[PDB]
Image (cartoon, rainbow over all chains, first blue to last red):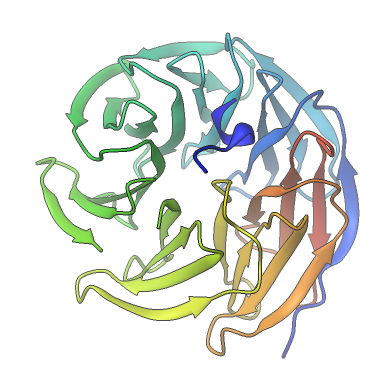
Amino acid sequence: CARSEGFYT
Amino acid sequence: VKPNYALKFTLAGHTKAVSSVKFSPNGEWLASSSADKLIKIWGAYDGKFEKTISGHKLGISDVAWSSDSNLLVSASDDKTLKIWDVSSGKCLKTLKGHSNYVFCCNFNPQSNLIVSGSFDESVRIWDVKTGKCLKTLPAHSDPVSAVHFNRDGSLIVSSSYDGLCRIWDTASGQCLKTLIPPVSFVKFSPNGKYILAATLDNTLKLWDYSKGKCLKTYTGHKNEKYCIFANFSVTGGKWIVSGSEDNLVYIWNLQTKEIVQKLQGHTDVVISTACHPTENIIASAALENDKTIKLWKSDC
């Protein structure tokens, strides 16, 4: 799941 | 005037992070999507669990309703979108075309089209009746965080981690406007005259898109990591609603930009909030350490 993970510093 | 949202129900059932919550246009239901690869339907007024809808191979990032409340569309990490019949809970069509995780989705007001945004940096337009891709926009240079149709479905607003908000003409696929920090969320105001955009610098912005001007700035919440949904609450007083990385739901006075209420109940980041179309009802959903949806009700 992309939304629940988040991303880039 | 300040709202008085009070916790009414906690909707437990998801086994992993909840990613999105949406009320049906008819005000009867709530749909939730989750990292557990499931969609749950619940009663919008009582929080009563109704159904589990399964089919996706990986976690679901978004879910959206058709105008007649009979269909749902989901955006999954499996690189697909699925149109479901809410009555049977069965997958009618599987929308294939995206080369990476499908992050966001929406039907148009007519519910004959579906707009989708993905990590493949594109925005796709699909036909509901055939499950065919009609237009593939090379919309952005980083993952597409949000996609939304306006009041008449003539415009599509998209956002992305590239830091841009783009307004597109639906039938021609042309870019009409590019508004110049990662943009984590975007949507049109109910009247379609404004856009509300969240950026990863703990900021919400109300824009008059044609004039290319920011009219209001909303802050005080935490948002530097997640693509958190934000809303216009119009059934009572006029408020801006949004989840936060501090596990609260924030409510701002639309005119003064002052925080009017912080809703405490969640034990993880509030990734999504939805406002009931007819009653002063807010649904909030949280991530991995919480996995529940909460329903809050107010006088105004």
